[PDB]
Image (cartoon, rainbow over all chains, first blue to last red; front, side):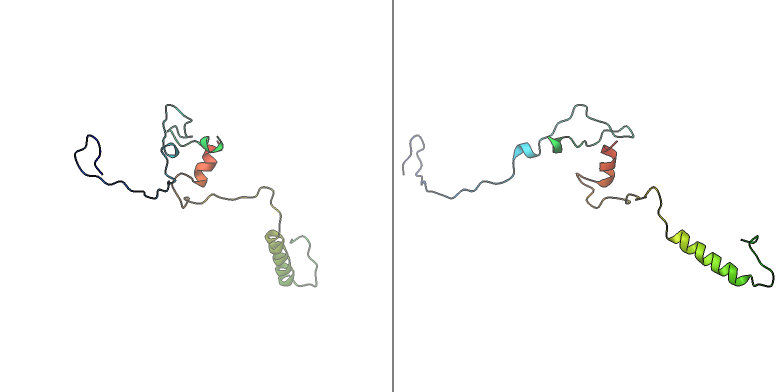
Length: 51
Length: 58
């Protein structure tokens, strides 16, 4: 096939596509000032698990 | 134990019986507050931990 504004022969076919589980919103994270650990250092808080 | 003694009687058998009975009584008992020490370290050590859980409790 001769496309437009390409000047190079090209072939277009049909292929099978399957989506995947990996998503950007499942690992994105940010933190300004959350709960602090007992010692005083910042630590992970379990709030996202309970929505 | 010594106050409860009788003349014309043995002593060693009495002592053995009372010691064994007290030992069994100590072994079989119902303590008020049950204890359960948390382990040295959680196996996963990533994104979850029993120590981490008891910390987020407080």
